[PDB]
Amino acid sequence: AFPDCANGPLKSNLVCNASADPVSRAKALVDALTLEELVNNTVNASPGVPRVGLPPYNWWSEALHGVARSPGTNFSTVPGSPFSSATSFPQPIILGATFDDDLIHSIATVISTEARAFNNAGRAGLDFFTPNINPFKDPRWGRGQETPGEDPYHIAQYVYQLITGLQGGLSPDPYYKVVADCKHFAGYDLEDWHGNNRMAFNAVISTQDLAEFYTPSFQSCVRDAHVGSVMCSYNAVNGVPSCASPYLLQDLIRDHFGLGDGWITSDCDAVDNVFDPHNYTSTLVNASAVSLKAGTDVDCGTTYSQTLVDAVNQKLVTEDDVKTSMVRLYSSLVRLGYFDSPENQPWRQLGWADVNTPSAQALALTAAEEGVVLLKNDGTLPLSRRIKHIAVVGPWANATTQMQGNYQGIAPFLISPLQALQDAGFHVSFANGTAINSTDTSGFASALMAAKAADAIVFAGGIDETIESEGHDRDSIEWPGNQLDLIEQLAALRKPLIVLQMGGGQVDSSSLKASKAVNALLWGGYPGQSGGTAIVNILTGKTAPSGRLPITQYPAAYVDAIPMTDMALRPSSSSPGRTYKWYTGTPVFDFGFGLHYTSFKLSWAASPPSRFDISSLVAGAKHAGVAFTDLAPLFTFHVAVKNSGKVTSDYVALLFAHTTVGPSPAPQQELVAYTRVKGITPGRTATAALSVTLGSIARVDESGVRSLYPGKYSVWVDTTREIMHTFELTGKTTQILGWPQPR
Ligand SMILES: *[C@@H]1O[C@H](CO)[C@@H](O)[C@H](O)[C@H]1NC(C)=O
Ligand SMILES: *[C@@H]1O[C@H](CO)[C@@H](O)[C@H](O)[C@H]1NC(C)=O
Ligand SMILES: *[C@@H]1O[C@H](CO)[C@@H](O)[C@H](O)[C@H]1NC(C)=O
Ligand SMILES: *[C@@H]1O[C@H](CO)[C@@H](O)[C@H](O)[C@H]1NC(C)=O
Ligand SMILES: *[C@@H]1O[C@H](CO)[C@@H](O)[C@H](O)[C@H]1NC(C)=O
Ligand SMILES: *[C@@H]1O[C@H](CO)[C@@H](O)[C@H](O)[C@H]1NC(C)=O
Ligand SMILES: *[C@@H]1O[C@H](CO)[C@@H](O)[C@H](O)[C@H]1NC(C)=O
Ligand SMILES: O[C@@H]1[C@@H](O)[C@H](O)OC[C@H]1O
């Protein structure tokens, strides 16, 4: 509910004055309240102040890939009633696999519209814990499915588009739409691997790796997309918990990245974790005091509302710190149109008629269509027009809730691969033959019986929330259970066999890759509510595959080569490396790898430059329409992408760069640009504009400073190195972006 700024008790307070400054309105509201009232409102499940007519407000609300279940959200218990469902989009891993920034922005707009519609019915808050922009650096993280991938630049572009779409633009032009919250600011990418609990895990991260990998996403989020909120994670960095670290929360988030007087929520009772089990403070009150002084403005729990009074009395914190945090929160609320009349807010006029819009359903289907990656095909795909009898088999064959991942809402419909095959008029023989993880072969027979008389076998399996989830990291990155045995038996029939590998993290498909009896292999991840229809549209040829792998499919033995606790990415005497840019082994399928139903010819649409002076680039940086030097351009490629095949398709141009200059070591590759050229009809030649900035070409040294270094740089366009171009930077090395040193 919202206050009554027309007749209620706050009507004569400056907080109810729309003409006044938002920060001044928050100040007027906070000065009107009692210190203890302020304290009992410093938590996510705030009760408001019944004296002044301030209604309750739950800050903990979830909408990762669509309006999700959360403490701040309820869905109508009646299945067909209004607000019983919401557009459940596919997991952000497949969404990053789309590599479509326009699509990500439109999805963010849909999510924000539906969140506003739910809030107008008293069924959702106005701030949402989204997105999760922690890089999926270790292949066996349970929550890496919630993230776009493993590339900090790709995640940066994703989060820029998503924040701008959710919040309603690059600025609160009038009011916010919804307030976002970039998740877990730290080196958080571990749940319980070998007993290392995130709530007691001490991540050791070098400043170089800190600024080069774990923070670019948050810098793009709060500095370039101007987010309204950030969340500090459970883990500790270099011995200090994040929510209690002034260097992480103040020196970087509020200052270097410029969150300013936006509000920082703690991970849910991570403030309590600072005491138990992080052991960091001797008393609980001291834990909450250090958390507050470090920058944590609101606690997702109950630690603040029952300890901050004692902290003020024990002189650990002052009344003014509580008032500062409350002013930040209430100022974001003022910007959300909390204290303004509904007559002047179109976003407050949204209802149930705006939720399951056909545009939203079609956009979810399109996201799934663009996100699925074709890993292998011998020409069996697209399915022959003469194929009529298909056998669908596997633990993912009739997937419905598995298709949603985690942090989801109740979808209006869950179209399974089986249901979609039936929707396309296929004579389907179904059998799930084995579970996700089991040794029971008793279903194999059924599978075989369903497939022995079929024109095509479609095995659909992999992993799901039973294998990877919040609080359960994977121990093996292989096909769980006896799934590979069933695939092998199906391949003994030597029919057209198509294997669908699902789930967030990758599983070792090298056995499938090497077997000639396996004709086609796709990765489906969590394709959302319309996932089956998208997969079948790709199979039949209705939609051409165009997605590309956002993460590396490591071979199995990788789990033995590096511990999940090793936060360093570079190789060494005990590290094969991390991610595509440092890994020294031979991945089964590379980052950015993808197949199409058509062949492409890539050339130059404009002769590329080959020489740049660093000082000239830095000087011209002040004249480009950017506010920070690292956002200024270095150059823009114009690739000519010709469709030399016979099928229309989209193409994802993935501009990679490699240098041997600047700080050693220097990565293999680094995704410095990417674009999605949509719908290239056969024969036609479309132009791909690929823009590289100074911040993506510069190098991060031991000090964590981003600077330009002279020498030879090479750049190519695909994982197959379609075209390549080598230029040189000359002149003197110039610092582009400083870095506050650890306090
Ligand atoms: C808001 O305050 C200003 C003075 O700061 C006053 O002139 C204006 O009338 C007030 N608006 C309302 C709606 O009371
Ligand atoms: C503290 O919070 C409780 C809700 O659990 C509320 O009843 C009480 O009034 C709050 N204290 C003050 C001083 O408002
Ligand atoms: C959802 O709304 C109904 C009535 O609007 C309310 O009674 C119920 O408690 C809400 N659900 C939750 C989980 O708060
Ligand atoms: C950890 O807790 C123990 C008490 O069990 C205490 O003696 C020790 O000083 C603590 N160490 C740290 C680093 O918190
Ligand atoms: C497929 O799943 C749906 C929902 O889980 C269920 O209603 C249906 O019976 C299943 N189909 C088969 C053939 O098991
Ligand atoms: C597929 O598995 C579900 C439970 O996982 C079960 O209800 C269903 O019966 C299975 N399919 C068949 C054909 O038995
Ligand atoms: C399969 O389940 C077992 C527990 O029964 C688990 O230890 C193992 O990690 C799972 N396999 C995979 C590949 O995740
Ligand atoms: O990632 C967060 C998780 O740690 C918490 O337990 O639930 C809310 C999420 O935002």
Image (cartoon, rainbow, N blue to C red):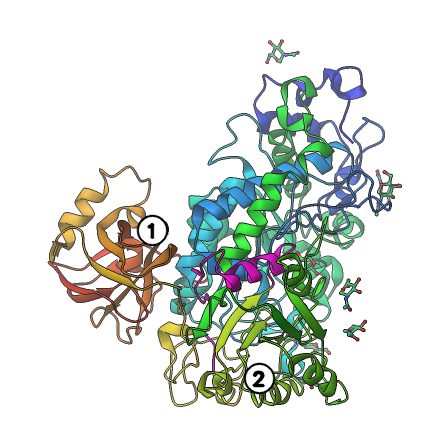
Instruction: Name the spot of residue 377 as percent of width and height, x first.
Output: 44, 74
Disc on the earlier residue, 1 or 2: 2
Regarding mark 2 in the picture, which secondary structure is present there?
Answer: loop
Q: Which residue is mark 1?
A: 681
Q: Which secondary structure, mark 1?
A: loop
Magenta span covers which residues?
A: 526-554
Q: Is residue 458 magenta?
A: no
In this rendering, the answer to whether 470 lies above or below 415 is below
Q: Which residue is mark 2?
A: 478
In the picture, measured across the screen, residue 445 lies left or right of residue 637, that is right
Where's residue 237, x and y in %? 54, 68
Q: Residue at x 37, y 76 (%)?
A: 582
On the image, which quarter does residue 628 sit in? top left
Q: Quadrant of ligand 7?
A: bottom right
Q: Answer yes or no: disc 2 within 8 Å of ligand 7.
A: yes
Please name whichever residue, 16 or 727, is drawn nearer the observer in this view of the structure: 727
Residue 646, percent from left and from top: 34, 59
Q: Position of residue 534 (x, y in %)?
A: 56, 57
Asked if disc 1 and disc 2 are in contact, CB closer than 8 Å, the reply is: no
**Majority secondary structure of magenta residues:** loop
Amino acid carrying label 2: it is Glu
